[PDB]
Amino acid sequence: SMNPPPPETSNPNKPKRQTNQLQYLLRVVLKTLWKHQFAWPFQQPVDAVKLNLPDYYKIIKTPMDMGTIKKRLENNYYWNAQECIQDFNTMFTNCYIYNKPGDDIVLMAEALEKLFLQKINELPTEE
Ligand SMILES: Cc1[nH]c(-c2cc(N)ccc2Cl)c2c1C(=O)CC=CC2
Image 1 (tube, rainbow, N blue to C red):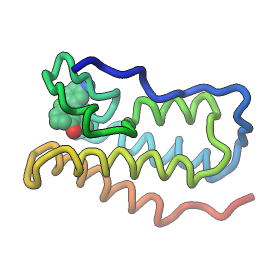
Image 2 (image 1 turned 90 degrees about the vertical axis):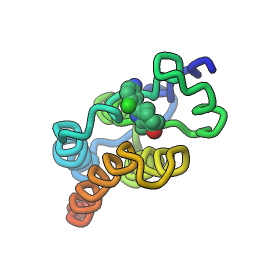
Image 3 (image 1 turned 120 degrees about the vertical axis):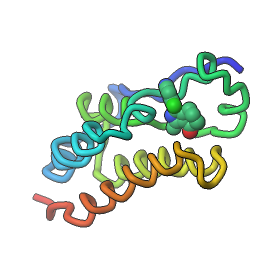
Image 4 (image 1 turned 180 degrees about the vertical axis):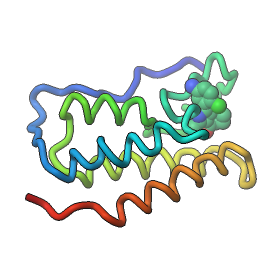
């Protein structure tokens, strides 16, 4: 029923790069999803204590959220864009795994994911 420590957003021994694809993931994908009307449940880790969801982290073992993604992009945490894409996809998957189908929270995840796929469809060419 307690909250776990959040996902790591800084690892100085982890090699990093500043690429046009990673810049796109911040300037376009993260910003588009962040300003969305349905973004707010995904802007920070699930607070299982205040939400009284004691089984959330019993079930969700790779928690992920756009607050964590944002910090990772700002801290230049990633080596490539696929890592960051995987974080987004894990956050959507967590929501679909934990919640019942037809829940409003699932509809919010779906709306954000639709936009996500639209932006990733036009990921720029490297270099
Ligand atoms: C992704 C998510 N965000 C949130 C959420 C997270 C914070 N921190 C605040 C308010 C909400 Cl709705 C939830 C969820 C769930 O999946 C579980 C159902 C409701 C809680």
